Amino acid sequence: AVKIKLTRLGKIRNPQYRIIVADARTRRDGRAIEVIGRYHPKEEPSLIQIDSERAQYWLGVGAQPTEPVLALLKITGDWQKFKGLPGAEGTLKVKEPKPSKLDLFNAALAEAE
Amino acid sequence: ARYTGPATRKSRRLGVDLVGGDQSFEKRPYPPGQHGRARIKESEYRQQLQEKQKARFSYGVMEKQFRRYYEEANRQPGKTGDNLLRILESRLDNVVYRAGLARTRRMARQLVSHGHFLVNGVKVDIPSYRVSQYDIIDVKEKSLNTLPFQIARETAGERPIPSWLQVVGERQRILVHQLPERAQIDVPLTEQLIVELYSK
RNA sequence: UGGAGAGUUUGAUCCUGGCUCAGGACGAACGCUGGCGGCGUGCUUAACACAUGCAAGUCGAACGGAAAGGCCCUUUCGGGGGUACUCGAGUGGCGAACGGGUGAGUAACACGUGGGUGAUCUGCCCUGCACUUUGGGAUAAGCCUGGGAAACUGGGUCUAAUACCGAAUACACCCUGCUGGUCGCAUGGCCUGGUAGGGGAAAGCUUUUGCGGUGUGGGAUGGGCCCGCGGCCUAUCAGCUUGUUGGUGGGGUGAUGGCCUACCAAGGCGACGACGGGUAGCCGGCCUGAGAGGGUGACCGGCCACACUGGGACUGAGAUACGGCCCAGACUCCUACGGGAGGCAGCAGUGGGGAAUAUUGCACAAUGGGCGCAAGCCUGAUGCAGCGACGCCGCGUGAGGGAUGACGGCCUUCGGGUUGUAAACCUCUUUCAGCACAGACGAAGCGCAAGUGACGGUAUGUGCAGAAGAAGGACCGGCCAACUACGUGCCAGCAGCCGCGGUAAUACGUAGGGUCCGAGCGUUGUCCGGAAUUACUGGGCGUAAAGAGCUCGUAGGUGGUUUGUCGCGUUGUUCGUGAAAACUCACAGCUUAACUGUGGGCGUGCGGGCGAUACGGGCAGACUAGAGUACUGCAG
């Protein structure tokens, strides 16, 4: 059975994962058929990217997500779109962008004068 | 580690003043030790090495760090000499010193290492920290009333602040517009000699 | 983006030519010394022998059951019955072929890259269609009993199933005969072509988000087999081969095939190095280099091979079956001598070998995996921690002021100079350590329970005190930064080379001074560079090493002028591939950096299509300047 797993990357303290499609018999860090997203739980909103069409294709041929990957697929709405139960709603909480350094630079300059 | 021994020794050996305003170097501008008066044999290697020692004892950078800096500067697509000079100038302690907030580079390094400063809203205590464009270096509120910063904030008539830096706040804020170019560096010595030495 | 030289042959010179040195790197070891942190990394030798403990189980929603908890009836407190919540042992299913280790063997389709399969398999997973009918015989367990020291094992009786077995149906499938169309790349393939004959299965459970069984069509995944090309050293290894080379009929296999076999034919390979010998896991990569190239295969990642040694099959969708079976052998252990047991190259650990390489730690919290409807269980995979300056990176050991420049040391021309702004003193700051308080993220997770982090009360943050607890190593004649004194005298010793020791050594030993590095500094070992010193880039052969004694000629290499054509080389473009990681460019995140992530480039190649025809080549011609023949003379 081909499965949609999470392989581990990053250094010791900070695990950063890749959402890979691979056979269930291969090791965690083995060769991957495809890479269809990444997942970084160390961030405050825990960035999640999933390539929707490839995920749809791999679910269509019958890949089985693991529990963390199933949770992620529900969050991004891909799982619901594949099934069709509540609709395809994006529940993804994207990280709030940080203002530019130039904005703060001019703000400080204006605050000086 | 760090170099803690006498500072005047290096100035006397290298034939130039590195602190900037020291009277002992003027009193005796010749190398230290018993044989500080002997004539020397001339060798290109000696001149290149002394130029490198000047550079890395002005900024207080050890040899391994200096070699890393040279590799980084050579890798960059500019020219090696001014790239190395700008990398050396972008250090946090050097920025603090050129900002008029420290009489000498050693005390600037000591202040930075003690975490008396704060870059971009987050405490930084790393003398080798490199400073990028539009960087705001601030003194933390607790240490604003200390005597070092006191005498730094009431003697703002010393060495001019270079163009690429600008103190804007009465609390002695520092703003960095862009990384300095070779024209505005205003440093002793010759970068070409260092480049020649490190290609040997 | 990008190549640095120096010393040494001579009385002196130039050249040729070797030797040596300055650089970088390491899974390192050794000497002296040693504060901290982050991130990595650690038997390279004996694929030597292994004490001990863990490293593969799970399902009561398949089954008979009731050994242990729960509940309920009962009691003489010995206990007895029921229950099915639950569950030991047992039958049954799935897993155990993955994951983890090692590099012994292997010079090979093992590996890398690109193809082919009209010559093939694929459990679980997804998705169409059709079904899920009917009957039977046992047996484990239980009970009784026997043998044996033990391992283990015999007999009788008894019981269930999704265990096992017979039949029906299927006509989607398998085989055979005839037959149609169609595509080819020849055997052939396709149209589930048509048609006649024969034939091939299944299993129930559970009331709850309900799980299952069989055949068949198509996906997805994982393979198998064949082939082109590519990467070692050795003719002081020239012959090798007899199922060996090909055919036919059989057999065998999932599949083609001397894979096996009977007969037949006599082939097949080899100087483009067969057959032998030696060495070796291969690669992405790593180190070095200006590049070409050279060396290498540690970590991480892919493939292969093996699991005490050597053979063998079995079960299964799948087997080198590490923690399966059978036999033989060596070794270790038990034995009542009849017979039995074992396999660390899994994780720790022990002994041995060695210059040399670690804890018999914590947790399933995260990720991956197995079983289960699920809760859940298992997981020395993994996530962490411990130890070792083993490596990279970062930080500290204080900062400012401080003089006709104190003491001491050392040198002295006896004047003084140097250590030296160094010190003493006056202020300042506390990084890191120490103490106190608070205290994480990693978990939009898991759980229908109320909770859940091994790391860890760590990182971190805030207060407190005080410069307070924090520097050594090599070298100093030249290469090659850095010199004096005393001691010794061809000794003791040093040394990479040149060479230094003969009472006045800048070369030995020690002290002052100095220089280079710095929690390191040196030594040894190994590889690349310097080395244009194997020279493709990029060398040479009169006398320095180097033209065979000279010809003929085989394979090979190479080839005048010109016309047409092919598009093999060559060249342009496009598509597929060239895993990730690594490298490089840019950006982002760790207080910075190392490190990590993201997106390009790179992946120098190979396969398919399309374009070009100058050159090289092939094919078909033409020409005479090369080459040869003819004729007339000529010298020897």
Image: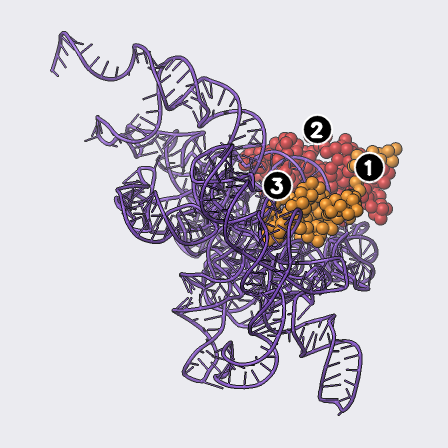
Chain colours: A orange, B red, C purple
Q: Chain of mark 3?
A: B
Identify the secondary structure beneath mark 3: helix
**What's under tag 1, amino acid-wise?**
Leu
Tag 2 residue: B183
Q: Position of residue C268 (x, y in %)?
A: 32, 41
Tag 1 residue: A104
Quarter occupied by residue C88: bottom right
Q: Nearer the viewer, mark 1 or mark 2?
A: 1
**Residue C349 in the figure: left or right of residue C21:** right
Tag 3 residue: B67
| Above/below status of B84 relative to A7 | above
Quarter occupied by residue A109: top right
Which of C209/C421 is in front? Answer: C209
**Which quarter of the rendering shows the C terminus of chain A?**
top right
What residue sits 73% from the left and 47% below the top? A83
Q: Chain of mark 1?
A: A
Identify the secondary structure beneath mark 1: helix
Q: Nearer the viewer, mark 3 or mark 1?
A: 1
